Amino acid sequence: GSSGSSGGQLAQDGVPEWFHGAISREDAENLLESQPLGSFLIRVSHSHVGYTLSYKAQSSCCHFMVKLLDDGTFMIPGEKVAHTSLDALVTFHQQKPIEPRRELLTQPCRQKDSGPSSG
Image 1 (tube, helix red, strand yellow):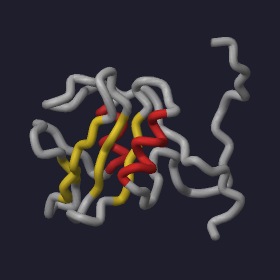
Image 2 (tube, helix red, strand yellow; image 1 turned 180 degrees about the vertical axis):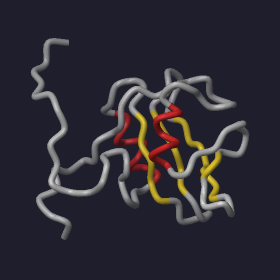
Image 3 (cartoon, rainbow, N blue to C red; image 1 turned 180 degrees about the horizontal axis):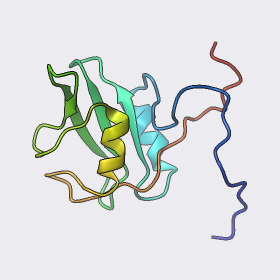
Image 4 (cartoon, one colour; image 1 turned 135 degrees about the horizontal axis):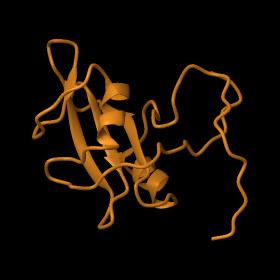
């Protein structure tokens, strides 16, 4: 691919890209579909308190549920390590895959919008 790029991450907000606030099961899968293998992302989980870590996998999009320990931390049901928050959980995931999925991460996904202002 010989596509052009800008390079760098310039934003005027206090929120990461991998954090798509609250998206729809489809939105996520669609956010990675047009993304290169490895592209990960997270979305606020409503069904069960906590979050849901997902990312593009060689085979197909993967969905991993994230519980919220009582110690104010987070740990996936099947791993042997935890993290204070998604942030500290996304970095460790870039080096260590998931119990079930031996796939690792590469870079955070970007919303399907630019984002002119908070509201």
